Image (cartoon, rainbow, N blue to C red):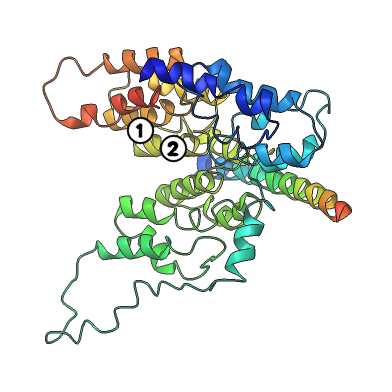
Amino acid sequence: KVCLYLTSCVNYVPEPENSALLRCALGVFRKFSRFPEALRLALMLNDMELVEDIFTSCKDVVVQKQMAFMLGRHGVFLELSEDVEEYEDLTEIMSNVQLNSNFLALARELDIMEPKVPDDIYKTHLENNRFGGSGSQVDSARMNLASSFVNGFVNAAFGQDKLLTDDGNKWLYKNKDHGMLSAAASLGMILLWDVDGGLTQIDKYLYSSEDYIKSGALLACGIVNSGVRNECDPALALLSDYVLHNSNTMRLGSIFGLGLAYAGSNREDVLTLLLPVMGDSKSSMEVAGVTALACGMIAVGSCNGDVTSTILQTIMEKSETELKDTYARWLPLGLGLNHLG
Amino acid sequence: DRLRQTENRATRCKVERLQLLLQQKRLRRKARRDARG
């Protein structure tokens, strides 16, 4: 029962904390009481993890899931004046950064798996054009994008296919502007969590003569940082300059990296960065929708200013029309996403 | 074409600076681990 959650989840709290001193089996199961009670109890996990200081290892196991396994949250909340014991290791854990992620995945994918994966999942149909006469009938220019997404999909964790996306490179300048955008995310979604090495592989596309390829490389920089809090902020530092770049489509997608790499936290700087497009009464509806899909879920919390901006921007063009579901496709989705969960 | 050349030059000097800072932080991280082992 709802009122029975509000007392049972807080009645869990003093039992393994006061009576027992297990002090790590509780915090894995005390995120149940994060949302229904209050934000104060949602942060008192960080509080009584701070005030408990029995050696180092057992509390390091507690913050190993506050790393990035449910919600980082206090992953920038520890440092005060180099006061917490092993602060620099606790921060390297909660940030998901390199040796606590990429190394591991690398330490599996080189040593337990096959690091080739050269699109053979879409090349295992070697027995189908002999089935039922002959083949070579489909000439539609849509298989190329889907095959591009497939071969850029399974090559995660350092399976970088340099000089293999040259079909995608030639399709950048040929046709399918949607597909030209969706093909440039292949290298970004191929070096997921390699923030330190992935930027050097994406760099070659940031100077492209095509807005689709350059936008897809900006989206790749966002994708690489998803779930990893790096001290150099390379996603914010590269995507910032493009958020307000032009009024057309390239205006539309340019926010989205900030919508992805900074969606599990709460910082005001990206919020006032992405706010002016959301609050200028711009009538291009898909731009407004994708900016709402970013800004309504940059922080899944209780940001009332973003709530007021979303609702005002909605009542800014939705009212005098009786038309399709695109009006409700993204902006009320973000308004729901502000306090969802 | 001139705007895009100034833009790509500004982006470049931003990326070249970020790569140096990431490499310096990565080397500091590694030096802490290699001193603990």
Q: Nearer the viewer, residue A45 or A302?
A: A45
Q: Quadrant of residue A281?
A: top left
Q: Residue A320, how many percent across, how many down?
A: 15, 15
Residue A1 pos. (x, y %): 35, 20
Task: Identify the mark at residue A256; answer none if there is no mark.
Answer: 2
- Residue A77 appears in the picture as rendered: no
Residue A303, percent from left and from top = 47, 16
Question: What secondary structure is marked by label 1?
Answer: helix
Residue A224, percent across and down?
A: 54, 49
For the residues marked 2 and 1, what is the alpha-carbon distance in whole angstroms? 7 Å
Q: Residues within 10 Å of mark 1 (few under 14, many from 20)?
A: many
Name the residue beneath numbered marker 1.
A290
Subunit that carries the residue with mark 1: A
Specify whether disc 2 shares its chain with disc 1.
Answer: yes
The label shown at residue B10 is none
Query: How many discs mark residues in the rendered view?
Result: 2
Amino acid tagged 1: Val
Quadrant of image for the C terminus of chain A: top left
Residue farthest to the right?
A: B35
Q: What's the residue at 35%, 33% (across, down)?
A: A290
Residue appearing at x 19%, y 79% in the figure: A136
**SS at mark 2 in the image:** helix
Of A205 and A85, the residue lying toward us: A85
